[PDB]
Amino acid sequence: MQDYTVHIVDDEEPVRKSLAFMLTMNGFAVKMHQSAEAFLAFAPDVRNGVLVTDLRMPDMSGVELLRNLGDLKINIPSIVITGHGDVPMAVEAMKAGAVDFIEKPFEDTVIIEAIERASEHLV
């Protein structure tokens, strides 16, 4: 079995805990990052990790984080959680290289399947 870690970067405190705790209960290794900046600083140290973003403040959406990761010359399979009915965010996430986007609200089974799909991109 592959020992990978799901790295959750969520701006809204409560939502971050909700997703992380839910993944934790399903047996995933999970690490919560307090901010996009914190994750970027940690990114070069990531081995066998999948990234899940739920960034709402347009100051650094998941798309900008993906772009910044690209500049660091680091690739991490990423799922970008997008706003309910937000078409541009989803389109931009896929254009930026996300393995998939997930529009909110989502079922736990759906985000879990996306994360497993993204983990398949790890060597």
Image (tube, rainbow, N blue to C red):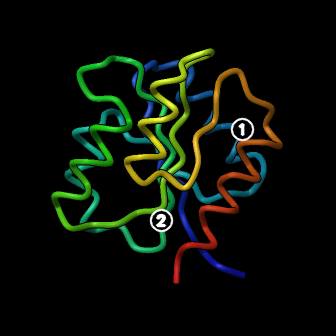
Which comes sooner in the sequence, label 1 or label 2?
1
Residue 11, compared with residue 69, is above or below; it is above
Q: Within 10 Å of the Cα at label 2, are there few (<14), some (14-19), or many (20+) other Cα atoms? A: many
Residue 74 percent location from the top left of the image: 27, 66
Residue 35 percent location from the top left of the image: 31, 33
Q: Type of residue at label 1?
A: Met
Foreground residue, 2 or 96?
Answer: 96
- The residue that mark 1 highlights is 22
Residue at image x 66%, y 37%?
A: 21
Distance from disc 1 to disc 2, alpha carbons, whole Å, reads 18 Å
Residue 18, compared with residue 100, is above or below; it is above
Residue at image x 25%, y 48%?
A: 67
**Quarter of the view holding residue 19:** top right
Labelled disc at residue 86 = none
Residue 99, compared with residue 61, is above or below; it is below
50 left or right of 74 in image:
right
Foreground residue, 114 or 5?
Answer: 114
Residue 120, compared with residue 82, is above or below; it is below
43 left or right of 54 in image:
left
Residue at image x 63%, y 36%?
A: 102
**What secondary structure is found at the residue carrying circle 2?**
strand
**What secondary structure is found at the residue carrying circle 1?**
helix
- The residue that mark 2 highlights is 49
